[PDB]
Image (cartoon, rainbow, N blue to C red):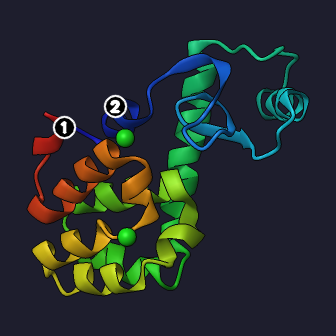
């Protein structure tokens, strides 16, 4: 199991513009297009992103290209972030995947806001950090995915995904 297979399980693949769980315009593997209500604001963002006139539809290859950019952008953001970097460095390889998953989903700023949880992961107080992470809008909005991530942090294995 690797970060890519993990995010592919959590986000799915869709070759046509769609609305995310929050109601936003998305495409491919979790690639947020815009928070704007306009399908048109979305179609334009999409063509800017792909470099062609797509008319809301892309190929698998194109979805995977966007996915590779997003994962890379996610990793570089963590390593560039003064709150996230130290947590990441302190963690083992599996747990590192769990942090990248949250960042991809909620952005650097979002995750950086989970102050207490970050402090507990850094101290390797697993069960405690799992309990605190569950007290969030995130967990209440997408409980099945939150739980998977959270178990990954609690245990350090890929069990939730297997
Ligand atoms: Cl809560
Ligand atoms: Cl979910």
Query: 95 left or right of 86?
Result: left
Q: Quadrant of ligand 1?
A: bottom left
Q: Which residue bears the numbered disc 1?
A: 161
**Is 85 located above or below residue 30 in the figure?**
below
Residue 156 found in image quarter: bottom left
Q: Is residue 100 visible?
A: no
Q: Residues within 10 Å of mark 1 (few under 14, many from 20)?
A: some
Q: Name the residue rendered at 56%, 14% in the picture.
A: 60
The x and y percentages for residue 28 are 58, 26
Residue 55 visible in this rendered orientation of the protein: yes
Q: From the viewer's perspective, tell me whether residue 30 is left or right of residue 101.
A: right
**Gap in angstroms between the C-alphas marked 1 and 2:** 8 Å
Asked whether, in this view, residue 133 is left or right of residue 142, the answer is left
What residue is drawn where x is 44% and y is 26%?
12
Q: Are marks 1 and 2 in contact (CB under 8 Å)?
A: yes
Secondary element under disc 1, as helix, strand or loop, is: helix
**Residue 9 - label:** 2
The relative height of residue 4 versus residue 135 in the rendered view (above or below) is: above
Q: Which mark is residue 92?
A: none
- The quadrant of the picture occupied by the C terminus is top left
100 vs 131, nearest the viewer: 131
Residue 128 on image: x %, y %:
16, 78
* Residue at the (30%, 54%) spot, across then down: 97
Q: Position of residue 20 (x, y in %)?
A: 59, 36
Pointer 1 or 2: first along the chain? 2
Where 24 sits versus 118, above or below? above
Does dot 2 land on a helix, a strand or a loop?
A: helix
Q: Which residue does the image show at 31% across and 38% down from the upper left? A: 6
């Amino acid at each position: 199991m690797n970060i890519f297979e993990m995010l592919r399980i959590d986000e799915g693949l869709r070759l046509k513009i769609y609305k995310d769980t929050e109601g936003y315009y998305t495409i491919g593997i979790g690639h947020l297009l815009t928070k704007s209500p306009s399908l048109n604001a979305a179609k334009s963002e999409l063509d800017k992103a792909i470099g062609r006139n797509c008319n809301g539809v892309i190929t698998k290859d194109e979805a995977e290209k966007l996915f590779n950019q997003d994962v890379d952008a996610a990793v570089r953001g963590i390593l560039r972030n003064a709150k996230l970097k130290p947590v990441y460095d302190s963690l083992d390889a599996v747990r590192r995947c769990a942090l990248i998953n949250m960042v991809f989903q909620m952005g650097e700023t979002g995750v950086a806001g989970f102050t207490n949880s970050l402090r507990m992961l850094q101290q390797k107080r697993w069960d405690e950090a799992a309990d605190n992470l569950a007290k969030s809008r995130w967990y209440n909005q997408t409980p099945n995915r939150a739980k998977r991530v959270i178990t990954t942090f609690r245990t350090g294995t890929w069990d939730a995904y297997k």
